[PDB]
Length: 49
Length: 46
Image (cartoon, rainbow over all chains, first blue to last red; front, top):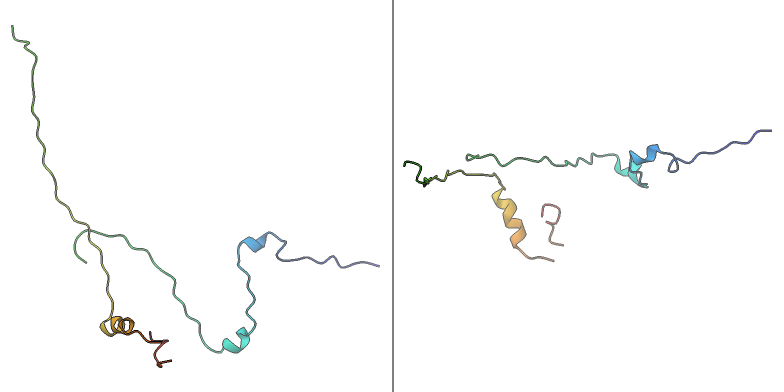
């Protein structure tokens, strides 16, 4: 016969790139947008803005 | 006889400069935080 050597994703290396988190009710709440902005830095230039 | 150890008195000046920044909010926006309230139908907007 032959076995099926399973592989875990968290035990891989690629997992560093993404943060995985389970969201149970998403498919229900996915009917609308979530729409969060993030940031943008800005220097303090001289002269009045 | 002309060596006569020398002396000097140099002077400098300051230089003015400014460093500004910008910031803005809306008027009614700021009003919502003043009122202390424990709902009152305004949490999300608050």
